[PDB]
Every structure is written in C-alpha cells, then in structure tokens.
C-alpha cells in the first residue's frame, strides 16, 4: 500500500455517518485525485478501498506496521459503553482497534466533531458511551489534532496535513486542540449580516420580509456568536454557507453542540 | 475447485458503514447468507424529548452519503404533523436539491464504490490507448483520443511503479482473477472515467450547495418551507443550471455508456441476485400531501407480479427485532416503534444485526432503483419506459434480465438518466413560477401539543420514512425506517430472509479467498449501514 516516497495515511471509520469522508472528496485545488496519487498514499479507507474482508485487514496491518510510519486520520466517535460492543469492525471493537493503532501513528488527526468531541451519537443520553478520540484514548497518550465541524471544511484538513508535512509538526492549536489558523475567529465576526446584528435588525421569522432582506438570524437561533469556524471566509463547495442560504448556524464545530446549542431555533 | 465452507466478509468495503456478510457455500455456490450490521448509534433514543424542529438536524447525520435525504424526510414528517402546506417554491427547491443528490450519489456509487468489483485497474496498464480510444468514441457521442487515455495510463503507471498502491492494495483483481472478464482497453476506459468522475462529482455536489448552503449536510430546510431567498435570484439559478447541465452530460455521455459496456461483458450476471418483492414511495411531489402527485408514484409488488401493483398502505409496515440485537421479539409499526438495544453477539439467541427487519404485510421487500424503475415502468411512466426499453434493446436482453444483480445495477443508471432529465423540467417549472410573481418560500405554522406525522422520501437507495409522535409539543417518539433497513436488515420473526440475504443464494464463488461475486451482489444494492441502523 506504501513505502518510501508518498507519506502513508491510514483512515479509520468509527461511529460515523461518512459525511466527513464525503467532505474530503469535495477537495478543491488540490482535488482528491491529486491528493491520492501525488500528495499522499491512502493506504486504508473502507469507503473507497478495493480490498474487503481479510484482504482489507491485511492491508491495514501492512500499513500500520510499516517502518516508514503513517499518519492516522480518524472519523467518528468511539463507542465505549458495554466494553465497546456497539461498534465493531472485523469483529473487533472500535475502541480496541483505535487503542492499538493510534498510539503507533506518527501523528493523529481527528476529523469531524464526532471524532474530535463525540458528536451526534454522544448527545444525551448517549446510549453507546461514544467519546472523542482524545477523551477515549487519553490514557494511552494520544493527542489528536482536532479538526471540528459536522462535517468540517475539507480546506481545513488539507491545510493541516500540508502544514504538518512541510513543518514536521502540528500548527498552533487552540484550547480544544483545533488549528488556530482555521478556528481562530467566530463565525459571527466574519458574517456579512454583522451590520444588521449591530443595528439590532433581526429577522422575526423565516417567512418575514426581514429574512428576505437578509437581516440577522440571531433571534432565529443563530449560534455564530459562540462558534469557532472559517465558514463565511472559505465557504463550502466554493459557493455558499448556512447563513448566506438564510439559515442559522447550529454551532457544529463546537463540543457537545447537540446539547449546548439546542434548541437550534432559540437564543 | 469448488469450495465448501463458510466465507466471511468483514469489513465489506466500498459501502457506507459497517457491514459483515456471512455465507455458507456448498460446491462453490452460496446456499445460505446472513447480513450483519455492526455499528449502532441510537439516534432515535437521542431524539426523545427534544424539540421537533431540531429533529432534521440530528437525523440528517444518520448518513452523509445520502446527505440531505433525512433532513428532507424529517422536515416532511414535521410539516405533516404540524399540518403546514409549504409554498410551491419550497417544493420546487427541495425537489431540485434532491434530484441533484441522486445524480451525485449514483455517479459516485457506480464508479467509486461498485466498479472495482468488475474493473481490474492494473490491467489498464497493458492496454493500447488508441484501441481503447476507438472503443470509447464508439459508445458515446463524446470523442476520446489515444492521447487522452495515454495520459491516464501514464499517470497510473507512475502510481503503480511507486509500489504504493494505496486504495488498490490487495485488490481482488491483482495478479488476475477468473471472475474479472474485461479486456485491458475496457479497463482503461473505465479507469479514466473513474478518475474523471472524481472531479465531476465535485460539481454535482456543488449544485446542492447553490440552494442548500453546503454539501455534505445541507442547511436550508425549515418546517414550513426553505430559508434560501438567494435561490430565487437568476444568478443562483444560473449557477445551478450550469452545474446540472454538466452533470447530466456526464450521466448521458460517460456513465450510461460505461454501464452498458460493462453489463454487456458480464451478461452472466443476469443469472444471479434476483428478488421477489418490491416497494417504493414515489418522489418529486406537486402536492406534499399526495404521494400519487409525485413524478414517480408509490407502489408495492409481490412475487414479481407487476400486472397487479398494489397500493402502498403505510399501516402495513412493521419492523421486526427477533433476529436483531434489541429486546424481545415483537414487531412494531413505527408510530409504536421501540429502540431498546440488547446485544447478544453474533448469532447469540439467533440474533446477528443492529438493523431491524422491516416487513410489509409480513414480506421482505427490495427498495431502491430497481423497485422505483420496475414499478414506474409498470405504471406506464413514459420516460422510464423509453430509457428502460432502450437499455434492454442495447444489451439484447428481455425484461426478465432485470431481476438480478446486473438488472439492479442497470436500473440505477436508468433512474439516473431519467432524473437528470426531469431536473430540467422542474427547473423550468420553478423559473416559470417565479416569473408569475410568486416569491414566497416559507409558510407560517404552529406547533401542536399532540400529533402524529410521517414523512416519505424516495432516496437514492429507496423508500425512506420518518415517523413522529408529538406529546406536550416535544418528541414523544421518533422512528426512522430507512431503505437499507428494508434491503439489508436481517430475518424477521417468520424467519424470512431479507432481500440481500435471499439474493445471495446461488451466487457462484470462484475463489473463496477473493469472493468478488458476493461483493458484486451486495454492492448492487448500494448498502448504507449508518442509514440502516441509525
Ligand atoms: S462529524 Fe458530522 S458529518 Fe462527520 S461523521 Fe460525525 S455526524 Fe457525520
Ligand atoms: S446571522 Fe448569525 S453569524 Fe451572522 S451576524 Fe447574525 S448572529 Fe452573527
Ligand atoms: S452550522 Fe457549522 S458549517 Fe459553519 S455556519 Fe455553523 S459552524
Ligand atoms: Mg429505525
């Protein structure tokens, strides 16, 4: 799967919806073909790899044990209730898999709010005892770089990997272990509706003429003021982002947002 | 070389989510099968007691492959519970985004998930690109040249001589494989298009973001309508339209010709993976409260009797747990549903999956593109009939060929082609409505203290339903019944094999260590286990 030349990436899927994997396929300049063929060696990824079953497990083993080292990118939370049985691959629990592989990586990136902070399956009452990677594996010394969002901007993943490959180190990280170069500003301070906010001009409903005219969505629940992400700047798919589509920010790059930010349509 | 024994495929790759397939094979043929889903999240549990308006944001995270679909189903569900009739334009915009989702989804499935079961990408290195270019140009209005294809080969050559095969590591086709039939040239055309498809899908997904904020996980739906006033502007419509037109071109000139070439090379696959019963919910409404107002209409068929399509009765759906890791053995209608996990390990107490087993009038039902296509065909849908007949005619087979793995794969393409066209029709109706001076996209509504609602979506993998009971203005019960639940769930308390399990019986297996034939059938259903289990 790899050797010298391209750095090896092992991509793991835990308790996830595959939205994070899909976000990476939306990679733009560079595109995912450039990334898979020229930048990196994607040596394990269950969504797109050719091998299955035992052949897939052997590819993983091959990749993790390589003397050249590997970077791990992790999607999804780790179910820990009942000894991890709510999530298994190859009849091993996700907890066990991550416990064994992640301490061997040269670097670990937790990609998406599920892997960084626990995410949707960790929302109350958290029946599977889902945890973010760093929470789950604290005791083994794992310190993943957290790239949050549901899903994150793929610009942020590629940017982080490129930094690491250039500098052989993580970029500056905030107190939630997120790169400051992407998560240093609130959504709100970057938002085109901030003049309306400042003027106290709020849409009272989605049907209102105030909404039509692009007034601030705070009264309709917008979590922009309490959410750290680069959405208004980079946008998504090179063309839009939630508030420009008329909908409040739901706070999706923040820990426990499912419980902290709800009800989504209230402030 | 006819193997007798078990085969286990875990993980099943090139699907969404965590699937374990177990088969018993006798003399090189599958004689028994189990579909085991090995991740549970419990979103239904998590939703209890929350604001019904919040449901779509949680349920959308059921799945990021069929992103948007669950947001749509939950919004339709709460719209229904609340009794709101959303504006015309909300219906148009929601339909357009959904049509875009189908194009994105099916294109990625065929190339990036299914094709490696049938294409030996390394054999593309042995190809003559001039001959390959001749072939490509003969199956498509799009002219492809030797140099075009040589560039792809060149790129692949560099990739393979680095010894870092990446996603192709340990592929079943490496070194050759008796069930892989394509010639080098065809492998090269497929490989080029795979690559091409990685960039084209960016545009297909962007089309959703034009109106829907972002992909994955759109953020433009609300109870009562949509939020995206910018979607009314000529600029955004123009942007959408140009992405749609390029996507449709790819569907028509790249995807379908490739599908046809491959089907023709694997015509023995008309002999395996058929199923008996079909269900579909219809999609793309004119009237949010009348399924029969949809471009594709709902319907139910038993034992392949398409001359007697039965009406879809939503009360005849029950989800079994006898062979699932939930408490007890009682099947439940989703308005009375229960999600009570109880793990027993594999085949403990005859339980082997985190998926429930939905049954309709007690029968296991296939849903997805083959159900949508066959039933629509049988309802006289003229677009579906035209495309279907043409496909059948090009492959030189009769309609009975559709009841198989090949048929299902073809049906996915047929549905893509029809929807790609119908998107243009909806787009025009949308434009027309705006030009009449209708600029409304959201309607007011009020939350009831007590109510029942259901929302229906025919998603790319089939009939999706979300079911709510509102109590005290909050979520008292919320149940998702998802296409892959129908198709890939386990046996029921009548021990009826599910569609995927039944379809596997009779599958030939040339090499038990590289059981591509099992993958071919499983992948033809386009499994999504996050969806199935939620
Ligand atoms: S962070 Fe969001 S998009 Fe990513 S796996 Fe989790 S639920 Fe899906
Ligand atoms: S719409 Fe949201 S992010 Fe924008 S100014 Fe208002 S509160 Fe801030
Ligand atoms: S919902 Fe998430 S995608 Fe950006 S606008 Fe808010 S952090
Ligand atoms: Mg369910």
Image: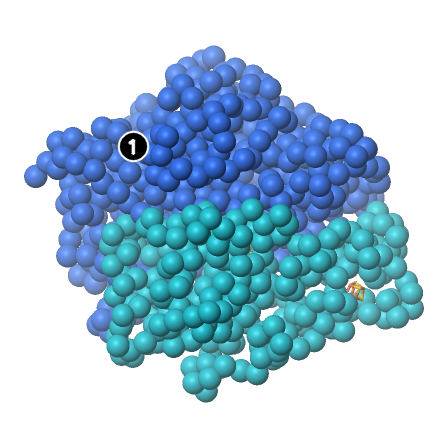
Quadrant position of residue B50 = top right
Q: Secondary structure at mark 1?
A: strand
Left or right position of B136 against A143? left
**On-image quarter of the N terminus of chain B:** top left
Chain B colour?
A: blue
Spot occupied by residue B54 in the image (x, y as percentages of width and height): 71, 46
Colour option used:
by chain
Q: Is residue B461 visible?
A: no
Please tell me which residue lies in front, B249 or A15.
A15
Q: Position of residue B271 (x, y in %)?
A: 25, 29
Residue at image position (56%, 35%) is B339
Query: Can you identify the residue that label 1 sits on?
Result: B33
Q: Quadrant of residue B520?
A: top left
Q: Of residues A264 and A237, which is closer to you in this image?
A: A264
Query: Left or right: where does residue B316 sit relative to residue B406?
Result: right
The residue located at (66%, 30%) in the rendering is B454
Q: Chain A colour?
A: cyan
- Residue B460 left/right relative to A199: left
For image coordinates 62% across by 26% down, the residue present is B336
């Amino acid at each position: 799967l790899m050797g010298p030349r391209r750095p090896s990436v092992v991509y793991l899927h835990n308790a996830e919806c595959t939205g994070c994997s899909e976000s990476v396929l939306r990679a733009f300049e560079p595109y995912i073909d450039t990334l898979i063929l020229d930048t990196l060696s994607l040596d394990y990824h269950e969504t797109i790899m050719a091998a299955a079953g035992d052949a897939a497990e052997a590819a993983l083993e091959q990749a993790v044990n390589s003397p050249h080292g590997f970077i791990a990118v992790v999607e999804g939370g780790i179910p820990t209730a009942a000894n991890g049985i709510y999530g298994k691959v190859a009849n091993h629990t996700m907890l066990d898999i991550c416990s064994r592989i992640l301490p061997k990586a040269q670097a670990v990136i937790a990609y998406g709010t599920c892997a960084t902070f626990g995410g949707v399956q960790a929302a109350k009452p958290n029946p599977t005892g889902a945890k973010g990677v760093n929470d789950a594996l604290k005791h083994l010394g794992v310190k993943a770089i957290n790239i949050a969002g549901c899903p994150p901007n793929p610009y942020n993943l590629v940017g982080t990997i490129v930094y690491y490959l250039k500098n052989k180190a993580a970029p500056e990280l905030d107190s939630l272990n997120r790169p400051t170069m992407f998560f240093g500003q609130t959504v709100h301070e970057q938002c085109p509706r901030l003049p309306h906010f400042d003027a106290g001009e709020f849409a009272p409903s989605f049907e209102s003429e105030e909404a039509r005219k692009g007034w601030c969505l705070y009264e309709l629940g917008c979590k922009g003021p309490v959410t750290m992400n680069n959405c208004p700047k980079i946008k998504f798919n090179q063309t839009n982002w939630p508030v420009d589509a008329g909908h409040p920010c739901i706070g999706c790059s923040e820990p426990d947002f499912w419980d902290a930010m709800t009800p989504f349509y209230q402030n | 070389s006819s193997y007798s024994g078990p085969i286990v495929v875990d993980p099943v790759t090139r699907i969404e989510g965590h699937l374990r397939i177990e088969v018993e094979v006798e003399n090189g043929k599958v004689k028994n099968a189990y579909s085991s889903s090995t991740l549970f999240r419990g979103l239904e549990i998590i939703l209890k007691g929350r604001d019904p308006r919040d449901a779509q944001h949680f349920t959308q995270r059921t799945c990021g492959v069929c992103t948007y679909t669950h947001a749509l189903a939950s919004t339709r569900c709460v719209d229904n519970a609340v009794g709101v009739h959303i504006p015309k334009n909300a219906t148009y915009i929601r339909n357009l985004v959904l049509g875009a989702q189908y194009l994105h989804d099916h294109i990625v499935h065929f190339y990036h998930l299914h094709a490696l079961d049938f294409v030996d990408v390394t054999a593309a290195l042995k190809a003559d690109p001039a001959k390959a270019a001749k072939v490509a140009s003969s199956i498509s209005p799009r002219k492809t040249t030797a140099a075009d294809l040589k560039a792809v080969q060149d790129k692949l050559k560099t990739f393979v001589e680095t010894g870092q095969l990446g996603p192709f590591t340990n592929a079943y086709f490496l070194g050759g494989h008796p069930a892989y039939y394509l010639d080098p040239e065809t492998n090269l055309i497929a490989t080029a298009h795979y690559l091409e498809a990685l960039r084209l899908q960016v545009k297909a997904a962007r089309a959703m973001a034009v109106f829907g904020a972002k992909n994955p996980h759109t953020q433009f739906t609300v109870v009562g309508g949509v939020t995206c006033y910018d979607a009314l502007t000529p600029q955004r419509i123009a942007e959408f339209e140009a992405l749609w037109k390029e996507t449709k071109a790819f569907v028509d000139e790249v995807y379908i010709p490739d599908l046809l070439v491959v089907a023709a090379a694997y015509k023995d696959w008309t002999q395996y993976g058929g199923t008996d019963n079909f269900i579909t919910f219809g999609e793309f409404p004119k009237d949010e409260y009348d399924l029969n107002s949809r471009f594709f209409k709902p319907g139910v068929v038993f034992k392949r009797d398409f001359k007697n399509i039965k009406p879809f009765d939503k009360m005849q759906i029950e989800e079994h747990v006898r062979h699932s890791w939930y408490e007890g053995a009682e099947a439940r209608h989703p308005w009375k549903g229960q999600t009570q996990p109880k793990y027993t390990d594999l085949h403990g107490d005859d339980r082997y999956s985190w998926m429930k087993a939905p049954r309709y009038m007690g029968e296991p039902m296939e849903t997805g593109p083959l159900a949508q296509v066959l039933i629509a065909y049988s309802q006289g849908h003229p677009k579906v009939k035209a495309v279907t007949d043409a496909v059948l005619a090009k492959l030189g087979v009769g309609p009975e060929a559709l009841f198989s793995t090949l048929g299902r794969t073809a049906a996915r393409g047929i549905e893509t082609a029809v929807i790609a066209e119908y998107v243009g029709v909806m787009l025009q109706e949308y434009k027309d409505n705006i030009a009449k001076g209708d600029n409304v996209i959201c309607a007011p509504w009020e939350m009831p203290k007590q109510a029942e609602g259901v929302g229906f979506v025919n998603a790319p993998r089939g009939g999706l339903s979300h079911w709510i009971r509102i109590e005290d203005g909050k979520i008292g019960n919320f149940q998702l019944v998802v296409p892959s639940t129908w198709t890939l769930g386990p046996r029921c308390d009548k021990n009826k094999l599910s569609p995927v399990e039944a379809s596997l019986i009779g599958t030939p297996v040339a090499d038990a260590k590289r059981p591509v034939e099992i993958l071919r059938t499983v992948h033809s259903f386009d499994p999504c286990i996050a969806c199935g289990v939620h």
